[PDB]
Amino acid sequence: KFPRVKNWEVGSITYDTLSAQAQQDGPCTPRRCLGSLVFPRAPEQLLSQARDFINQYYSSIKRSGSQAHEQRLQEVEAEVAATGTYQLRESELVFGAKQAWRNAPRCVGRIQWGKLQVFDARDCRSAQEMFTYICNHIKYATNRGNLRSAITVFPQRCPGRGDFRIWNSQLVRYAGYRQQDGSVRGDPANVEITELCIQHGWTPGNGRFDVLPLLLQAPDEPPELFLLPPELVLEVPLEHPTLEWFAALGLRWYALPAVSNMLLEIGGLEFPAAPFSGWYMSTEIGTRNLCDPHRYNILEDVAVCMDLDTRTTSSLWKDKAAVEINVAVLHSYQLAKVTIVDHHAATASFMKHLENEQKARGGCPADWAWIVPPISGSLTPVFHQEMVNYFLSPAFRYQPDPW
Amino acid sequence: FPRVKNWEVGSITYDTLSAQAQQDGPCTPRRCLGSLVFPRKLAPEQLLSQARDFINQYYSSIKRSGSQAHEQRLQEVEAEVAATGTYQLRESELVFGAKQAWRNAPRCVGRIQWGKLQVFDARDCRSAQEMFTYICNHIKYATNRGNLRSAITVFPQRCPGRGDFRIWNSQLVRYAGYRQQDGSVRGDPANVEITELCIQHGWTPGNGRFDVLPLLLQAPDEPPELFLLPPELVLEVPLEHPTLEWFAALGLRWYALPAVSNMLLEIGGLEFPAAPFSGWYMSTEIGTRNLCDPHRYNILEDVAVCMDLDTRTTSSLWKDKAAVEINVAVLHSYQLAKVTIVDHHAATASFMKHLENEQKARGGCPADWAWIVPPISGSLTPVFHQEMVNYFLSPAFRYQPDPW
Ligand code: HEM
Ligand code: HEM
Ligand SMILES: Cc1cc(N)nc2cc(-c3cccc(CN)c3)ccc12
Ligand SMILES: Cc1cc(N)nc2cc(-c3cccc(CN)c3)ccc12
Ligand SMILES: C[C@H](O)[C@H](O)[C@H]1CNc2nc(N)[nH]c(=O)c2N1
Ligand SMILES: C[C@H](O)[C@H](O)[C@H]1CNc2nc(N)[nH]c(=O)c2N1
Ligand SMILES: [Gd]
Ligand SMILES: [Gd]
Ligand SMILES: [Zn+2]
């Protein structure tokens, strides 16, 4: 009844009993698997989710069945009956944010899941106070290059009030200016948000690494434009340890990966605004952000400077240029004393996580196509680890763009 | 109808062919098991219905459905199973079914070639010595002095009352793997079990890292018989690097012909447990998986040391630099020997074209993203950004239990 799961490098076999507890249904059926799709997608339903969360909390602290556990269950039942909703205790919120990270199947950094700084912003009341909370987040997490994981949780969704939203997909992003040729100067992934910042009063730049302002939405108000203080956004200029012309490319990236557009769901409550941040795995910058054809797309240019034969695929110039771009990313972050992890160290620590989670809960939801790095996949141990993908709550979820 | 997006281009298609998926895969709404290598698997009315669907497939594919020839073949099969318990495929039906099974293979990136397959009909095979003759002819035709040609040879269908034909080797060409005293392995670790079966059944073992194994062939209701491949039949490529002169001295080699021999072919209810097929290699199969996997030859650190890379820290990406040069050596050595090989960039681009072609021919294409995306430089190839739908159509190649 439980999926048998094999590691082909070592030969070992486990059974994922945790998946049987999967609380929501994914896209696959016995007739066809859709595991590679990027986006696949009251009172008594709220109560059964709340009850399950409270049960999770009290088990985490090994007080299951205690008087405090029973009373907290009764307390939540009474609040949902009177108001239609309930509030999390402070400690439940911290636990819930950590559990959501721990449950995120596509995250390879979950070895860190217990070391997460939770900022409680549930009494925020304006877009301006939102901005203050975000600046304190960026300050704490950046920590002058020594990165600390963090999440800031703004007020939960509630009836009769709009949501707090952060319109930006990340707290720090580079502008992408749509050209008349159909081309883009800057980051193409950010064309729409760039157009929305301009419409809302931002005087644009014309560089390739222009940091976008924040578009912040307080309940029942249009979004408000806030500029990030430049001394708060730590950036790394890219150079290569033995290719001195690389620095003349004029490349840079920012220190802090801070996703701001997902929804955090805890015990049936929904938090549409809850930015979270850790530190980068180098292949996200080197391979994806800089070499994706639809991103900055620098691969052919680096190869030509390296004087590779770009006229035939059989020279493996693409693989060679990509490797060196990743070397430069790693070298530049270490040189700038900004935390970063390479994809070998990251996937090694994830294997340690899988073994911890197997002992702790009997399984671990993992999306194989996202845990395997985008270069060198079979060189890392997760390639040979079979994985079971499924949805647990608390959870981080994708959500529609507020516009 | 699943909506499928290419994130590099922005294009959208709908896979209407998945609707016709015969059997059921491992996944449920509760959890996805698309990364498992083997799903935990391994009546006349049952046979006729599968036979019916295939005959209809065939006649539709030659624009003769509902025709006179269609209705006659249907009634012919009904009568043959009523009298025999099974039925026989027409030679053309066998060709069509073999090509379809390849075409429907979700994990094969080489399917752009699916129409060009040489089918060798061996259904009249009697002994293991005759099996060995059919095999050696396949190998010579498929190798073709290094201008590789795709091919399959079909041995007699399993039928009730008698044991099956089986090739015990997982491939026709396999290097031995010798369990060593200090726990380790000399040779290919994947083949430790078959290498000891060969020794058990008589084979005198070598002691190299690339001793080609003999073939353990099993006729119906017989013990397996050892057969030695003639050396001039097994084309091998010694591996050298275009600029690292010391690479040749590592003594690495690989063989020209990827010929899988332990999978079962299913056509319209019929099952052929011995039907070996072959194409040519993609370079990453050799250079990345077979030589660099930790549980295979595992040569990565060896090459990195010869390159004077800093193996002390993972962030020098010495594993990545060594891997790229091993794949370069593979491509260079195959091309130099004039043996057919394709790099993962060229291959993935051809599969994109196959996806487009199948979208018009059949409305979709079953594909297993985890196996289509190459094991190095995944996101540098265009299949990485292609969403894919995996399902099982028949005719098909299937995994089967080992004969022991
Ligand atoms: C501490 C260092 C961390 C590293 C190195 C890391 C690494 C990664 C990587 C490489 C991905 C794949 C993203 C992509 O390729 O697009 C990812 C996804 C993700 N990570 Fe982590 N992460 C870290 C911390 C965190 C934290 C602190 C959280 C939240 C508390 C988090 C939650 C997520 C989520 C929710 C996703 C994507 C989920 C989805 O798309 O469905 N991560 N992470
Ligand atoms: C002619 C050029 C061909 C190329 C370049 C090619 C390439 C590949 C590759 C890279 C795989 C992934 C297997 C792995 O490394 O794990 C594969 C799998 C497969 N191929 Fe193709 N192949 C070719 C021809 C063929 C032919 C002629 C057949 C049969 C008619 C075939 C049927 C299959 C099947 C059934 C699999 C699945 C193997 C498994 O999952 O066990 N292929 N192929
Ligand atoms: C916290 C954290 C650290 C890190 N190093 N990387 C991350 C990547 C994402 C991410 C999620 C979904 C989609 C995308 C863009 N494809 C990126 C989220 C959080 C991350
Ligand atoms: C025909 C053909 C051509 C080719 N180039 N490669 C192939 C690989 C396989 C294969 C089968 C089982 C396991 C693995 C490795 N996990 C690979 C089968 C047929 C192939
Ligand atoms: C089509 C494919 O699933 C999609 O492009 C995915 C594949 N795996 C990925 N894996 C990670 N970590 N990040 C990504 O953006 C993607 N893209
Ligand atoms: C666990 C995972 O499914 C397994 O390691 C797969 C992944 N993708 C693969 N892809 C190919 N071509 N060959 C393989 O052996 C594998 N192994
Ligand atoms: Gd230099
Ligand atoms: Gd030397
Ligand atoms: Zn699935």
Image: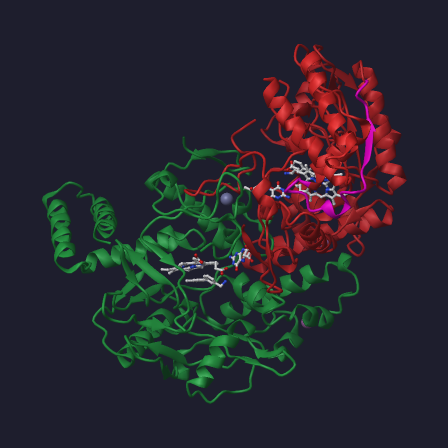
Chain colours: A green, B red
Task: Where is residue A160? Give x, y as percent.
Answer: 23, 69
Residue B153 position (above or below residue B249): above
Camera sees residue B110: yes
Residue A137 position (above or below residue A15): below
Inspect the magenta stretch and tell me whether residue A82 lies in it: no
Residue B46 position (above or below residue A70): above
Magenta residues, dominant SS class: loop
Task: Where is residue B184? Give x, y as percent.
Answer: 60, 31
Q: On the picture, is B287 further left or further right than A200?
A: right
Residue, x 60% and y 72% (percent of image)? Answer: A296
Inspect the magenta stretch and tell me whether residue B108 lies in it: yes
Q: On the picture, is B290 further left or further right than A91?
A: right
Where does the magenta region start and end?
Answer: B104-124
Camera sees residue B173: no
Instruction: Specify the quadrant that holds the C terminus of chain B.
Output: top right
| Depth order, front residue of A371/B96 | B96
